Length: 141
Length: 141
Ligand SMILES: [Zn+2]
Ligand SMILES: [Zn+2]
Figure 1 (cartoon, helix red, strand yellow):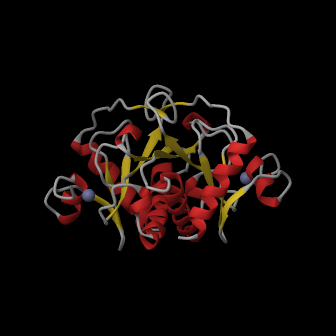
Figure 2: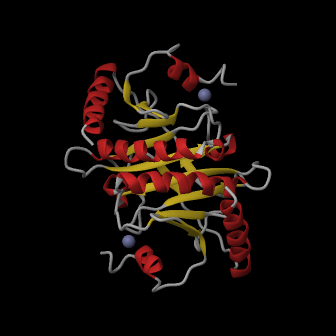
Figure 3: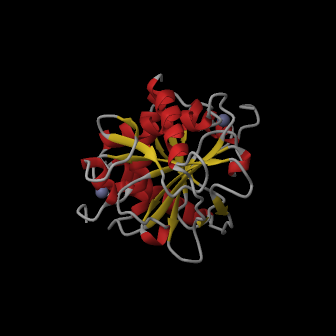
């Protein structure tokens, strides 16, 4: 559903939204449901539902816009802390089915992104297996 | 402290780590303290402590490697869900002072990245103010 995709609606002009930046392949704007003041979004213009569906040229342009946006979010003296978050799948907390990078200011212990970081044990043999599968997958793109 | 930066140590070869991919400006490898099985990291070779310190060319290369890595993480049939997370500042849960993108498989409600998503109200006037400041900041990069 690109038809029922609110970011496609913004991109084509069917819903208005103040544009923070625009490049050939990407757009930035403010999140109107922020976790903290200054929370923004960077999206590809292409309707990719997950990051792995995004084109390589689109990936270069989105990476560049993300870095530029982080400088905006870091503030005039660069002291503002922040989290970059991009979700892929509804189990992974993705709501709109279109790639979007959140850049979320962390002003406060009580506001912004709150993360649970509980690690698990993985074996050396399992790490090697995953490293092989991943590198071969990446090598053939 | 690039001297006490474990990712710089990996990058220069002072600590061994199976390399999942390597490009001119970026490296990928497995996280040895994973939140879920297959949790990996994508880092710039440059010692940038936060994303806003990263060069634009390095940003393009890291965006491309991130997209490639997501295809690896999505798996042979692309069904694996995942979160991309990059932290900037110790209040923002950044531990190693070198930019690193986590790509974290979400296999399970009980494993992988766990996120708290409590939004705050922002006014139209505040959104316009932030949009102006951000777009002007981005325009002059
Ligand atoms: Zn869309
Ligand atoms: Zn470093």
